[PDB]
């Protein structure tokens, strides 16, 4: 059905847009200017880019979450390689204090990061 919406709802929402050259990009909106129509998109990969809306060829909004259970006939809400059956629900309230999203939970004491580390620091021992 149709519902009333506000400009603040679009700000900070995650949408994807194709530019005039048929390239696609997605992220969460971080700024919008009515004087020159300029939009900054910040995506959950810690990357942000400022793009003027006039080069928007096409716009879409990605599903943040699914309200109903997944039967299988419908397509996946997001693009991923493999899903773990042990993991399914995240963030009991809304989000986590550490980072923007929680991933690689593992068993804490065992398998901290697939037995591999990029930076060295050793918090203890």
Image (tube, rainbow, N blue to C red):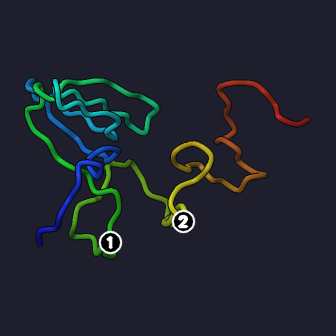
Quadrant assignment for the N terminus: bottom left
Query: Where 53 sits versus 11, above or below?
Result: above
Q: Residue at x 29, y 59 (%)?
A: 76
Which residue lies most toward the right here? 125
Drawn side of residue 4 relative to residue 79, left or right: left
Which structural element holds mark 2?
loop
How packed is label 2: few (under 14 Cα within 10 Å), some, or many (20 or more)? few
**Badge number at residue 45:** none
Q: Nearer the viewer, residue 11 or 88?
A: 11
Q: In screen coordinates, is 74 left or right of 91?
A: left
Question: Which residue is at the far front?
Answer: 35
- The residue indicated by pointer 2 is 93
Q: Going from the N terminus, do you reach mark 1 or mark 2 first?
A: 1
Locate residue 68, reporting x and y percent. 31, 75
Residue 58 position, x and y percent, is 9, 38
Residue 36 position within the rendered picture, expressed as x and y whole percent measured from the top left: 16, 24
Residue 93 appears left or right of 42 = right
Quarter of the view holding residue 34: top left
Q: Nearer the viewer, residue 6 or 115?
A: 6
Q: Which residue is mark 1?
A: 67
Q: CA distance from mark 1 to mark 2?
A: 16 Å
Callout 1: SS: loop
The picture places residue 85, in percent across and down from the top left corner, at 49, 66
Task: Determine the image quadrant of residue 52.
Answer: top left
Q: Residue at x 17, y 26 (%)?
A: 35
Position of the C terminus, as image quadrant, is top right
Residue at image x 14%, y 42%? 59
Q: Which of 119/26 is in front?
A: 26
């Amino acid at each position: 059905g149709a519902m009333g919406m506000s400009v603040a709802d679009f700000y900070g929402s995650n949408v994807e847009v194709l530019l005039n050259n048929d390239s696609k990009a997605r992220g969460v909106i971080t700024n919008f200017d009515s004087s020159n129509s300029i939009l900054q998109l910040r995506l959950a990969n810690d990357s942000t880019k400022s793009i003027v809306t006039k080069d928007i060829k096409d716009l879409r909004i990605l599903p943040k979450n699914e309200i109903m259970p997944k039967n299988g006939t419908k397509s996946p809400s997001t693009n991923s390689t493999k899903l773990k059956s042990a993991e399914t629900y995240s963030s009991k309230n809304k989000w986590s204090m550490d980072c923007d999203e929680e991933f690689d939970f593992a068993a804490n004491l065992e398998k901290f990061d697939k037995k591999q580390v990029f930076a060295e620091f050793r918090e203890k021992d």
